[PDB]
Length: 431
Ligand SMILES: O=c1ccn([C@@H]2O[C@H](COP(=O)(O)OP(=O)(O)O)[C@@H](O)[C@H]2O)c(=O)[nH]1
Image 1 (cartoon, rainbow, N blue to C red):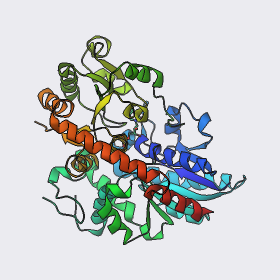
Image 2: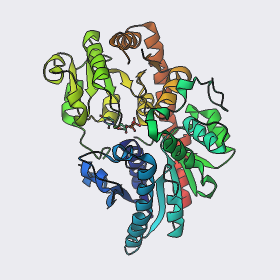
Image 3: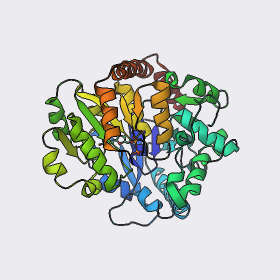
Image 4: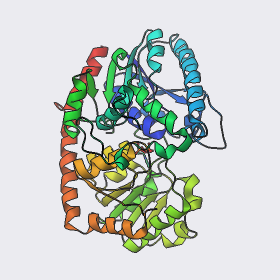
């Protein structure tokens, strides 16, 4: 087989979409080796069934308590991102030299677009280099314009809806790290003319005009949704799926703020009371390190009548379940795309980075969600949005719109669709 190496940035919203692409490629007969940091490997619980070799490299930055890589970087982003970079260059080089003593020899390196300097490692080692963007073309376009100096972080940009300042990617939320974060996002386009393959986790029908614009500059390959062995981490699948099976169609609010975002105890109390007073059934992912910010007795007693509070769920299987009526989300791109491709309308509560822009696209372009208004977002505001989605006639339109996007996404990934064709073109190029 042809041997593909894959190197995501060490965070679940970067690992998971690349894993799903790797599983598709392994189904076409390619051998896959996934490169992870030691810190990521500590959370990996299931890997045997997917058949992919996993090889680890050092973190390259300090190990603090049981914190994850981004959390450590936030202490000093400019210093620690560039320590992570130097270590990753050195140690991926060493790893590839070891892989070159085994058959089949590696031929291509698919690397996260946020790590553009890995291209030079691939080429130095005689491999093709493929940059994998884990955000949509519309948001990535903003980072390109930042690199060109057309904008620096109402705002008009080519082939994007008119934006309010609050809709631009949220870099101000990173405080003293804000300048470093803006620079790394723009750097995704710094060597794009040297990349052998440019891949985006999106599909053409979702953003026709900006994809066409981007394609007038570089040959890009839209391959999304990569999401269809589907999980590396503990998902509590049996508990979650048995509980959803006890629920009637269209009755459950799924709630998750992703793998990184953390809300204050003040904000968590507002969400807790909004869910209780709504009187709907709900499944709320509260990560284990965030549980201590919940109101006392919430997980053990008051959520027992109508809710399931869990530290991680099988999100693809949850969003596919007929009981789920809507998705209160932080609007990370994977959650946004997974919900749209499942036909599930959203309540948008973005926190930072691309989430703010994603929420504007959800509400105003794709029209499959409503957005909360900050005062802190209060229980009444959240309750209002729940009634809009679950009860009102507007909620029925949002659901019809979500089902339309689900059908276009099914088309894109099936035989003859744009993403299916693009993955075939990538695969045949390697052959
Ligand atoms: O209980 C959960 C919550 C999230 N996810 C997955 O975690 C990723 C979240 O990535 P996203 O882009 O939505 O936000 P981020 O964590 O990067 O902020 C996605 O692959 C979700 O499917 C999951 O499997 N179980």
